[PDB]
Image (cartoon, coloured by chain):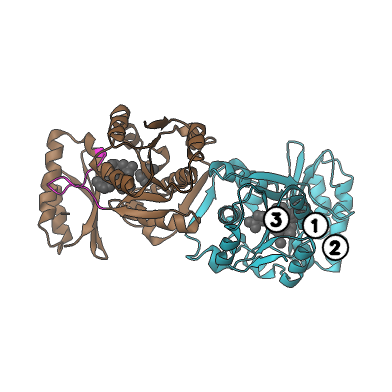
Chain colours: A cyan, B brown
Amino acid sequence: AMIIADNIKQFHSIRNSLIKQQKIGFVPTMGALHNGHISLIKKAKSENDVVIVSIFVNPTQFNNPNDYQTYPNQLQQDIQILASLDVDVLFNPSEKDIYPDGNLLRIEPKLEIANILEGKSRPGHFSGMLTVVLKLLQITKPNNLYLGEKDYQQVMLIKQLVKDFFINTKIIVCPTQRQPSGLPLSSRNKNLTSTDIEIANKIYEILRQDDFSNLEELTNKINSTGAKLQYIQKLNNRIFLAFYIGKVRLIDNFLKETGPS
Amino acid sequence: AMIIADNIKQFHSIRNSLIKQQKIGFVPTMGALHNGHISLIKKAKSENDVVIVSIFVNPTQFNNPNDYQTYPNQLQQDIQILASLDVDVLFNPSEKDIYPDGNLLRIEPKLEIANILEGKSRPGHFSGMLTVVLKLLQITKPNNLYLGEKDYQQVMLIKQLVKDFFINTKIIVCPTQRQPSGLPLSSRNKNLTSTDIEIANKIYEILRQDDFSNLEELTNKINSTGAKLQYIQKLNNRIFLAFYIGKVRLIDNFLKEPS
Ligand SMILES: Nc1ncnc2c1ncn2[C@@H]1O[C@H](COP(=O)(O)OP(=O)(O)NP(=O)(O)O)[C@@H](O)[C@H]1O
Ligand SMILES: Nc1ncnc2c1ncn2[C@@H]1O[C@H](COP(=O)(O)OP(=O)(O)NP(=O)(O)O)[C@@H](O)[C@H]1O
Ligand code: PRO
Ligand code: PRO
Ligand SMILES: [Mg+2]
């Protein structure tokens, strides 16, 4: 019963079948679906008449090519996961349908929140994500859109985007889903070995009780577990970080006062 | 009968009060209307049930400050003109309206056609225009967009923009309106002096005979008029050129065989 639009043409026909009198939620993803994804969907299903999920791994937002090839995909499973949530439409285009001409027109952010943290760390990542998210919104024309708090600046950036471009959509920000350790669910977590999860869980032991008072000391702890701490910083009440375990790269942010978990 | 909407909110309630059975044409402009502009509008009135003209001078497209200070305002004369055309809606917003938070998000082109001609001589300009046109379209949501062939690159660029961003609007291209001399109707012309105006026509009488076989010579000819030629080239079947007369900056493009 879930419909699958494999290309834009299919999706357009579906999309122009629905009335305006009714509510369309949209959850975009790169697939390899986990409990975090699933939470956004559920919430979408609670608030809307039609739920659209897209799965596209957008090339232009990967600054790291090996990351791009390394990126997990299991579509047949994602479809099964998606159909067991009674998702109405899976939009699953190819690069060729999103970028018929290649990437010739791009959103380039100039803001402070764009030059820090994830923005400094992955150059061009934000441009790419902003370009695809604009295109996805234009295609899906949703009433409601669901985003994880996990990628915080992503949310800010998309909030500005829909404002600046006069896109009529509510943005709902969903809380980050975590493991008991406090470790946030991530698709790239599939790529980490048993040895790494050990480290990862160690890191979160450290984070779970720590002051955040002294940041240089914490880096030292985290770097000692074998992961490479990339950035860690305080903004308002909130801590942000990124780090590598092996070749797998993970980000997190949470309220300083409460978290992770 | 013409609604003048000086802000987005006013404009929205107007935009969304309209039926699907009505076709909306849009003619974006920077104001200071001349017959070039009119020609576009006369063509929109003919193909549409509702015509929307906008006047916004977009700061973001200007790569020269004095060009921006220079840029001609006749707002009241423009309202008049737009009224004797029986234009339905005049949308003329302010900067706060269009860039509520400043200019944070930009359309940036990477293609050759944005790296040549007007693109070299006006850095930042194409990104500026693309951003405003995107906003303008996202706001007006029209069926038909009317653009002049005079800004050729821009036309090409807006054609890309529309296709890349999945906006359903037809692009309709309209022929350059000219003075008898062949000089293209232009807003900045209202800045030419009476003698500068005669220099323009000299330049165009020179263009009216050239086989365009030697451009350095055509160049020296143009420059001997007092003008300062910025560039001239053939790409495909056409000439593109731009030049200065004093402070005023003008451009053209046409088939090798400006009538
Ligand atoms: N643990 C999570 N809790 C809540 N939302 C999440 C979580 N993880 C991801 N999301 C959101 O799901 C959407 C898709 O994430 P996704 O695009 O698939 O790529 P990613 O962030 O680079 N790798 P991943 O960690 O799986 O998201 C985004 O809005 C994410 O913020
Ligand atoms: N002489 C002309 N003939 C036909 N169309 C024109 C002419 N001049 C301008 N237009 C078009 O009218 C629309 C608005 O132009 P405009 O906003 O005034 O920017 P512009 O290129 O600086 N125009 P201008 O300064 O008047 O030459 C654009 O699509 C133009 O290409
Ligand atoms: O462009 C993307 O892929 C990001 C990921 C979550 C939704 N938006
Ligand atoms: O209106 C504008 O912003 C310019 C001139 C017409 C098309 N682009
Ligand atoms: Mg994913």
**Which label's residue is closer to the chain start, 1 or 3?**
3
How far apart marks 1 and 2 lie (CA) works out to 12 Å
- Type of the residue with mark 1: Leu
Query: Magenta includes A244?
Result: no
The relative height of residue B2 versus residue A216 in the rendered view (above or below) is above
Q: Which residue, given by chain and number where applicable, does mark 3 sit on? A: A51
Magenta-drawn segment: B175-188
Task: Tell me where residue A46 appears, x and y as whole percent.
Answer: 77, 49
Measure how far apart labels 1 and 3 are at the Cα level.
22 Å
Residue A140 in the image: x percent, y percent?
60, 55
> Residue A199 at x, y = what percent?
85, 60
Q: Amino acid at mark 3?
A: Val
Relative side of A261 to B89, left or right: right
- Res. A185 mark: 1
Figure check: A29 above or below B248: below
For the question of whether residue A228 can be seen, the reply is: no
Q: Residues within 10 Å of mark 3 (few under 14, many from 20)?
A: many
State whether label 1 is within 8 Å of ligand 1: yes
Q: Quadrant of ligand 1?
A: bottom right
Quadrant of the frame with the C terminus of chain B: bottom left
- Give the image location of residue B200, x and y in percent: 15, 44
Disc 2 marks which residue?
Answer: A197
- The reply to whether discs 1 and 3 touch (Cβ–Cβ < 8 Å) is no
Residue that sits furthest to the front in the current view: B21
Which chain is indicated by disc 3?
Answer: A
Whichever of labels 1 and 2 marks the residue nearer the N terminus, that label is 1
